[PDB]
Image (cartoon, coloured by chain):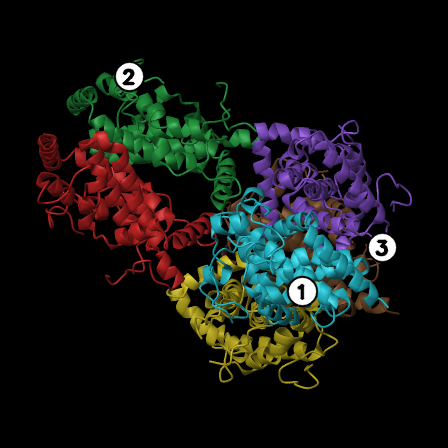
Chain colours: A purple, B cyan, C yellow, D brown, E red, F green
Amino acid sequence: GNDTTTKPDLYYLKNSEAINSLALLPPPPAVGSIAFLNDQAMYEQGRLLRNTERGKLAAEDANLSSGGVANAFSGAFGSPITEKDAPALHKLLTNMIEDAGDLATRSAKDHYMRIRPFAFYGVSTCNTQDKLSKNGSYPSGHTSIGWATALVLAEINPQRQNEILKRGYELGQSRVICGYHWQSDVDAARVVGSAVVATLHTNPAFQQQLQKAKAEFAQHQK
Amino acid sequence: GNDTTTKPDLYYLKNSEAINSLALLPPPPAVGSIAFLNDQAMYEQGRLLRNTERGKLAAEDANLSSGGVANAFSGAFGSPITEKDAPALHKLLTNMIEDAGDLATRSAKDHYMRIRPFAFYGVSTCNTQDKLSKNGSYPSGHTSIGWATALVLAEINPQRQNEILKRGYELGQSRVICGYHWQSDVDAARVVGSAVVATLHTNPAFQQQLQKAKAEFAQHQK
Amino acid sequence: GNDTTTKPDLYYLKNSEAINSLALLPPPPAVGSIAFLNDQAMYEQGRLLRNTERGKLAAEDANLSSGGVANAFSGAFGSPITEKDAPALHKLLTNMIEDAGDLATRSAKDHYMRIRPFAFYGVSTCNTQDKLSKNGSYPSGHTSIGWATALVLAEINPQRQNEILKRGYELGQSRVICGYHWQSDVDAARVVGSAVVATLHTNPAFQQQLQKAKAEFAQHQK
Amino acid sequence: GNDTTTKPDLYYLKNSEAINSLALLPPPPAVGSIAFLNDQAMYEQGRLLRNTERGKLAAEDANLSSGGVANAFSGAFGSPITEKDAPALHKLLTNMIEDAGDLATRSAKDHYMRIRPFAFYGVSTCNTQDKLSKNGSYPSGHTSIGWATALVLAEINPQRQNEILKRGYELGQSRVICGYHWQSDVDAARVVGSAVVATLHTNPAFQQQLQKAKAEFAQHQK
Amino acid sequence: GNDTTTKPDLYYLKNSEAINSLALLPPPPAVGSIAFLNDQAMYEQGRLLRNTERGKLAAEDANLSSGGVANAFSGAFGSPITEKDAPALHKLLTNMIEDAGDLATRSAKDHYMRIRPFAFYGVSTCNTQDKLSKNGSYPSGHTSIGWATALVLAEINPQRQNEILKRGYELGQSRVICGYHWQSDVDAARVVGSAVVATLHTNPAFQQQLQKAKAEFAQHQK
Amino acid sequence: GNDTTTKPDLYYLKNSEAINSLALLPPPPAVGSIAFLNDQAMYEQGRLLRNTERGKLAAEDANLSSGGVANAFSGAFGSPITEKDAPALHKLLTNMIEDAGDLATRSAKDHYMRIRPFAFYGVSTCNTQDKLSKNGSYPSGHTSIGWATALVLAEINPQRQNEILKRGYELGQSRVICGYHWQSDVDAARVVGSAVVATLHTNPAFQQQLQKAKAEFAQHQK
């Protein structure tokens, strides 16, 4: 039920402006399906990656809160994405967190109530610090945030768009490797995460904050 | 090799501005994988839908050329998307066709050279009028166009964003039902189709044409 | 819509007395499911059996009309099940054909409208003489008849109950081997085929005809 | 080795009168088969249902002993099935418990010695009060009892036949959801459970007890 | 039934000296198994390779008769394996053809009578010049020959053992790619093909012919 | 890095003489593949065999060190294969242990670093006395030893070649049943285990030791 009217620091949009995820998305793969067989195999594979350097990154990524995703792009972006160094940018990206994380995922989350892999398996994640929810797996709100942030970051810095998009992609993949999400939750999440950035471009406040981040970035360039 | 410098009526962007699809996307499911088993089952299911009213629409959609996608949104959009009735809009959407269809899909297309389902199966499509290519299935350039158009349309008309996005989604699904594309080609295509609309928002000409389509739409509203 | 009131030679029961197959049965396996993967493998296996002596029997069985099932038990039963030799018996078994074949399968048939294997595969059966329906596969009305007949036959001749039940079982298996039905259609059919024989035992006319078949069988025994 | 001659309170039939389950039934799905893959997925799905209201019922059903199945139909039947209220009926249903549970399942049970799901998985059931056997899974004697009871109940009260059959069906499904049995054990069990009610109708004592239950039910009706 | 006593030009060994393939080998994957699912996917994959340069080689290899395998190693071996150039060698390798092709595969061939992929699929091979047998697929006699020849060639020229073994391996893989054999037939064939070279080393005539091929090769080396 | 020059008691061959396993072998089945699905099912099946008499043997076999494989053939061979009773033979077989176990498996082992089943599953083996490695599963060095020993044993005693080869086969199968190895590791291992016996026949010391074992066996025969 929250939105910009209750939490204007974390949403630009209203409840009425949300992507209807329940309407747009396909249902998650069901148990008994081949597509779920594949979700399982992707789980086991990520599981085997846990011991690697990519595994290490995934555990780190899995430690990210919604709030740390913005700064999680710094390396892809080419420069620190921080309150200190890029305040107009940090503010932009923070203020859209729950537009992407909540508004864009909610109706499908709440309807399907899907069990996460670690919970399905009665194990823990690769990670494993908050009191982990077992549920509302589909789609991934974290992946929706990471994808939506990559799309707006790619627009601010098209010179590094590919690195940015790949980071965005990988944030979601980290959740699959660490056992937080099925591959399909993360895939579904990139669809709604894209849709919400269309809506954000209709929003005056977003528009203005984006201009500011662009201007900031520009001066940044010398 | 084409781009805006060779075909400025069908691209806003340059070769250098393209999404590196080969870099961003996962490889397509391989034969021997469970994920390919699923692509197959999705093929057979779409195949069984061919006889239905959804099957009818998919055959119609499958008749669309890149150029007919814009107008294919008219019902979702709420009003005719035509040269006659919405010229600023039609122009916008046409001019980005190959940004989405080509630039955003090319490196992965050309690298993987994937076989389409009808060709894999040695059958025809649900459709079946051009001399069908057997290949460069992954990702789908048609689905990339349809998704990217839905994202920019959703921005022009957020009141109908959900209907618009669902139409966009379904254009790609039509290609799976009709046998033109594997489900994974269409899924991959929505990722690059989103990425290219980020890039388009960095482009002055696009920006200006989008303002015009917005203004046109506005007067349209009475 | 037919029943005993329209076709009293082929039903004992009324429409109101039918097994609600749509209510009782699980849905058929869907395309995309592992259970459908198994239906497919059972298809291919039966297909390979077509060349054998069991294949020969299945083609013969597949030539049976509903009316020929009764006599199709003669060998299992131990003696000819014919108008000539066992008229009280033949009459009993004929008069319940559509109770089992129709009434007991109808609501699920008509609701699911499932595609038969030969039609799914765009091939023919092992058989292949009537104008084959592509559809209403689930459940199998022929298997429902064969199972229900085996149950009532087993009651008349418990000395040969095992041979009788195995024949009953195999009639349905013949339809899987020949490509007429998915294994799941035949399995579903044995459930409703059993349910309808419970109902038949509540029916005065059935009861009386069954007494006659028992008496006939008795004199048959010397 | 028991039968009516050793335990005439729990069998109507003799050893010689049993359904030869080993002869009639297909072998259970083997490990390495797709049909076993499906048994597994049905296990995991039931497992996810454990938390629901259907899960609650399944745990309750899983607490049933053979003796409590009769009364487990009371709601489907429309009235209490109890020694107190429906003694002729309760007696009928009790006296056939092991005809269905044992005689009808024995040869296949003992031959295949199949491992139950909880034991396969080295876990417990949804339930989990007796010292659980790991083995003789195929077919399910509990499901055979529940199905056979539904068939004879459906005959006593055809007005509620559909509710009765659905309850019967669900008793077996409870065992799949709770982890006691593979879906295939329960499916196999409905086949032999039907066969044994054919045999029961040949048995004088059963016939007479069934008449009594019918008469009792009749007076019950006012 | 043939052997060295009937065809001493094509066998060194007798019937009594054969590898009992039926005894040693596992059964082939059955339809309904996951291992057969994999045989199928390996079929489809080879099928897609048919258009490539590896596809070209496989079609060529598929044109080989048993008699042409020896010379088919010339490139791996480093020098022509021909009657003209390496007669002692050519003779050795020819004289063991049916030891490997027949004796080592026969009992399993004849027992299982397995259907080849092209026949299973009702299609042709990649090849497709003799009147193709549909059957005795398991194991592959051609692959048994190619593997057994690679093992004896590797012994004559250990400097090129790796190239030789890889050629040997690939001869069998060519049969999978071209649709002549399931992957499992070819795998099974390498087991019996190895076993028969153990037996060949017990055979005086083989021993002597092998000494001659070694001596010939030696002079070949300058 | 060891070989005959460092450990001449356990290798006949040098590093340069090794089978290039990385070059020859296919990659192991990947997670996400159907072939891995099959490796899993073979794991679960062996797992269910653990309780049987074959299970008992597999646990015993799993207790074998490389050094105990030679004597593990005594029953197949027909007579004790021991330092006491068959010293020339025991010496032969010992001296080739690491040719088969190490040299023939190394490059593929070290490259793929595959996880063993018990480790994949986070369980123990059927066995479970050394500090079990989790890794270098593909191919199995133990199976390579057992197969290579069966091939050289079959040559010494062709009268018992079939029993010998079947024992050889089963040694590897024991590792699958006990959870030490995937079926594919064991299959891959029989390929390289055959290749190394070709190389061994090029080695003077091996040749001479083999003559001695043959002579010993001969006198053994009376």
Give the foreground label among 2 and 3.
2
Q: Is residue A143 above or below residue B76?
A: above
Q: Where is residue F69? Give x, y as percent.
A: 34, 24
Residue type at numbered disc 3: Lys
Extreme residue in the bottom direction: C6
In this rendering, position of residue C127 left or right of residue C25: left
The part of the image, by quadrant, that contains residue A143 is top right
Labels 2, 3: one chain: no
Tags 2 and 1 both on a single chain: no
Q: Is residue D169 above or below residue C62?
A: above
The numbered dot on residue B70 is 1
Mark identifier at residue D84: 3
Amino acid type at mark 1: Ala
Q: Is residue C211 above or below residue F122?
A: below
Which circle, 1 or 3, is nearer the viewer?
1
The amino acid pointed to by label 2 is Thr
Residue carrying label 2: F4
Q: Chain of mark 1?
A: B
- Residue D70 picture location, percent across and down: 75, 55
Q: Position of residue E114 (x, y in %)?
A: 35, 55
